[PDB]
Image (cartoon, rainbow over all chains, first blue to last red; front, side, top):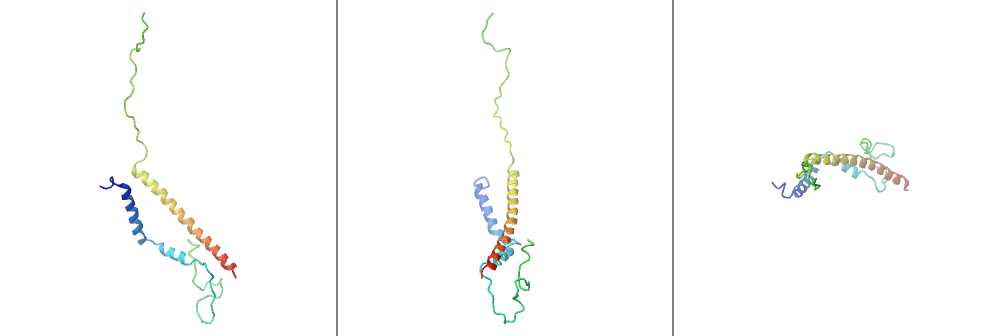
Length: 74
Length: 68
C-alpha cells in the first residue's frame, strides 16, 4: 500500500496518532499533577489560630496536615 | 629457438560477477534494537528526573526556611 509510497509520512502519522491518543492510558498523570502542584515557590503563609480547625498543624515537624510520602518511596 | 611472449599453457580465469554481500541487519531487527535502546534511555531518564525533582524540592525548602 502506501508503506512504499511515502513511508516517512506513514511513520509520522503513526507517532502523531499515538502522541494524541496515548495520554488516555496512564497511571502517571495523577503523579504529574501531584508533583507539579505540591512544589512550593512562595512563602507558605501563616494564619490566625482561632478558627478551631482539626487540621492545619501548628508545627512543621507535626504530620497532622496533608503531606507527601510517596516522593521518597518513588 | 624463438622468444616471443606467449601464455604459458593457459592462465587462470578472472571473475566477472557483481560480487555484493548485502550484509547487515534486516528491517525488523535493526528497528527493534533501536527502539529498545530508546526505551532503555527513556526509563533511565524518568528515574533521574524524578530523583532530581526530589532534590530540587529540597532546595526550595532551603529558600523557604532561610527567608524571614
